[PDB]
Image (tube, rainbow over all chains, first blue to last red):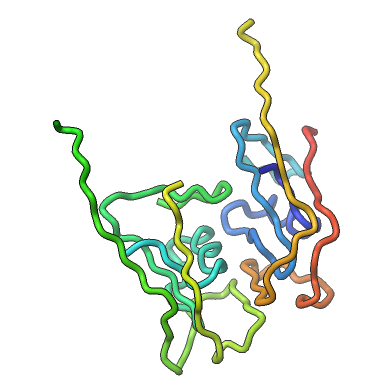
Length: 49
Length: 49
Length: 49
Length: 49
């Protein structure tokens, strides 16, 4: 599964916290990318691994 | 006892925080594993051990 | 002969019911329901994979 | 020939819909709309850049 979400409110949550973030909001949903190539994601100065 | 839970929400909050997850919610409940084997629970990228 | 197969036993309840003074030791779980009138009906189990 | 090309297949769903008991597990995000009639239209993904 690739990195997907529903709205950008969960993408900007996932970049802030990557351990305590929500995978499922009220109707909104976000899927963490699990893959062999662990892609490094930058969004401004927030960065996850 | 195995990792039973009465909702998806208790699973997805037990994956997030570990030392401060909720054992007993309002009407739902989750059950920590005290099994002799110890499995890592690969959920997205949020493991627990 | 040494590669033996120990087999344990696991157990978990399905669809229990908390007593009527309900509570919650959590913060970041909000369920769109009347909390004093909810009980489980299914149990979620994590697989081997 | 040591620089080979692996080809993974990535999939992600769009426009899904949660069950009617709708929960949340991040107490930080708050949308300024109704939570109960909330469902996504799209899916935000990330590029290679």
